Image: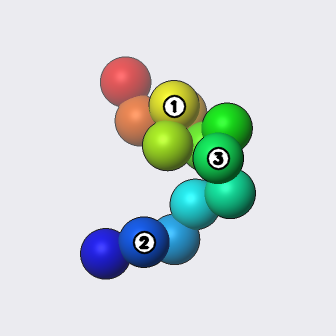
Amino acid sequence: VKKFPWWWPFLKK
């Protein structure tokens, strides 16, 4: 489910 800005999709590793 979407719950990111654009740069956060990053902050998951």
13 versus 5 height, above or below: above
User: In front of the other: label 1 or label 3?
Assistant: 3
Say what amino acid the circle numbered 1 marks: Phe
Q: How is the image coloured?
A: rainbow
Residue drawn at x 42%, y 72% is 2
Q: Name the spot of residue 13 as percent of width and height, x first.
A: 37, 24
**Label 3 Cα crowd, 10 Å radius (few <14 / some 14-19 / many 20+):** few
Q: Name the spot of residue 7 as percent of width and height, x first.
A: 67, 38
8 left or right, relative to 9? right
Distance between the alpha carbons at the discs numbered 3 and 2: 10 Å
Residue drawn at x 41%, y 35% is 12
Marks 1 & 2, CB-CB < 8 Å contact: no
Which label belongs to residue 6?
3
Sequence order check, earlier mark of 1 and 2: 2
Pick out the residue farthest to the front.
Answer: 6
Pick out the residue farthest to the left.
Answer: 1
Question: Callout 3: helix, strand or loop?
Answer: loop
Say what amino acid the circle numbered 3 marks: Trp
Which label belongs to residue 2?
2
2 left or right, relative to 7? left
State the image quarter where residue 5 is shown.
Answer: bottom right
2 versus 13 height, above or below: below
Residue drawn at x 64%, y 47% is 6
Say what amino acid the circle numbered 2 marks: Lys
- Residue highlighted by disc 1: 10
Marks 1 & 3, CB-CB < 8 Å contact: no
State the image quarter where residue 11 is shown.
Answer: top right
Distance between the alpha carbons at the discs numbered 1 and 2: 13 Å
**Label 2 Cα crowd, 10 Å radius (few <14 / some 14-19 / many 20+):** few
Distance between the alpha carbons at the discs numbered 1 and 3: 8 Å
Pick out the residue farthest to the top.
Answer: 13
Marks 3 & 2, CB-CB < 8 Å contact: no
